[PDB]
Image (cartoon, rainbow over all chains, first blue to last red; front, top):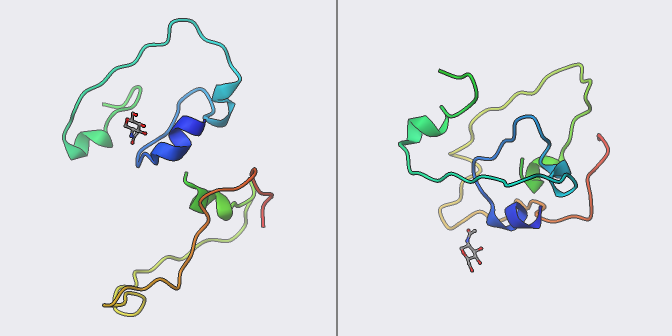
Length: 50
Length: 49
Ligand SMILES: *[C@@H]1O[C@H](CO)[C@@H](O)[C@H](O)[C@H]1NC(C)=O
């Protein structure tokens, strides 16, 4: 919570889990990806979205 | 969204609608307009209205 509150990311939306609830749940071995894309593609990453 | 969004929160049910229109020649000051203020931090969420 406090992490993304300060960072002020422009694009942020979470699927299948609420961002406010994220502090409560417990996971196993969270992954993290990272790359750089063109502007249009930033509005083009989503599950089942061609 | 951001805390500015969380300052004005609509109910889950809402009858009516919003109207938004551009304002570049009146609300923009060449020397810098700073009369508008927004909220960036708060204790918790807000009830609708
Ligand atoms: C960049 O990394 C530093 C590491 O000390 C961090 O403090 C800062 O918040 C980061 N900037 C962001 C997340 O915008």
